[PDB]
Amino acid sequence: SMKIDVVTIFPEYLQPVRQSLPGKAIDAGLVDVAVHDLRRWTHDVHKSVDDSPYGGGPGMVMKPTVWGDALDEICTSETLLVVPTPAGYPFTQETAWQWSTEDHLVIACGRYEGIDQRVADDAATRMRVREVSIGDYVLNGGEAAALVIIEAVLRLVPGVSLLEGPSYTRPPSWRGMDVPPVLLSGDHAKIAAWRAEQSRQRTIERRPDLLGFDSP
Amino acid sequence: SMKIDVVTIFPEYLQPVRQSLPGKAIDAGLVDVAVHDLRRWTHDVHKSVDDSPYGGGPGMVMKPTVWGDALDEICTSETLLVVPTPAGYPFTQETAWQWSTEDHLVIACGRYEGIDQRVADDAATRMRVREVSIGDYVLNGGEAAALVIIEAVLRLVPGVSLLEGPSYTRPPSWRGMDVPPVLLSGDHAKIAAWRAEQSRQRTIERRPDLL
Ligand SMILES: CCOC(=O)c1cn[nH]c1
Ligand SMILES: CCOC(=O)c1cn[nH]c1
Image 1 (cartoon, rainbow over the protein chains, first blue to last red):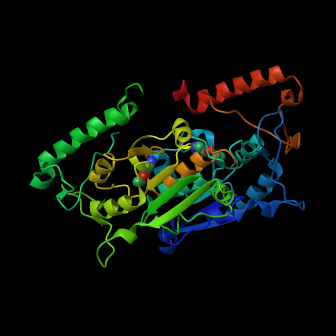
Image 2: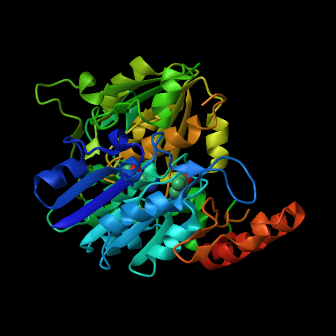
Image 3: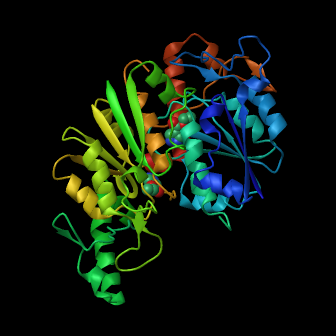
């Protein structure tokens, strides 16, 4: 069974929920997901986890010491350490398929200004490290990106190109709008053709990059 | 004050949590977020929300009569309707900035196989509709994508290029590794030039597509 550990200063936010895809996986016994409060590894009364950046700039950077103790306790040399960040290598469907065979994923959630770089540098001396982006926008912390990665990966676990065109179900006419009649005909070959053409025009319009063309 | 309505068959999973950024905004009174269970608008005892695809194929497609009623109740002509889908236009930082000044966002979460296309086509005749992808991977449903979109938009509400390089804070030395000396130099022109070169090298290595 696969084990996923998540580390965050917002533990309530990432606590697993029974009625969800990861919730079902856990219940089928196919995965163990544990959430850890980063503040468990702090010593001071005020339990501080970040500080102003060396060299100046906005916001705060998470301290290396606290992350060091957390990952020392949670990770082994076998661990794949996942770190969401706007500056990461791209997380894609290939990435999801690959991670779906892993024994132990640890996901380190940190603020967007970053965890002190020495943390990832240190971890890399003992385990495989993957800093990754799920897309080109900014989140305040890695938490929401962790939830996307967990969804993408777990649905590919055993036992759990081109854009898709429009899809339709009953009734065949609704508010004066009809389902494309080819879909009603039962001709497998004609239906395959119409769907291919629909996918072509959608991909060219919305995602020309996928077909090897310049973006808008 | 911004209003966000989220429509889903997984209401617990999407319930706001106090200990989060969206939870802070809500308690600060900068947004009101409302989560609705789609099953509220079903017709039968089974609370059916999908049905087999015309033309055949795997998976199921969400019913137009059910989503139709739900959006009639929730949306107004001022609504910007958001539909996460792998087939969408890309959601980017530019998109988040645009939506951050909207009065009413409604986010329709469905399974990845899709919602009957006539729902969006119908809605687009009396309100603004945006189908968007948050990245090139497959989720079972739009729920996690909605959390990401809400996160990116809300942090841009008042009150709540190249890649960024490495960042550092105290202590100066840790486990045999020193913060790069130039950052403690007090030469802020040189610091900006060093950070630009770090950004350039990191972008070459991790995202060469951005050049
Ligand atoms: C630490 C925050 O991380 C992000 O904002 C992100 C991750 N992927 N895309 C954006
Ligand atoms: C309705 C399911 O939505 C997705 O799978 C998705 C959205 N953006 N990237 C993937």
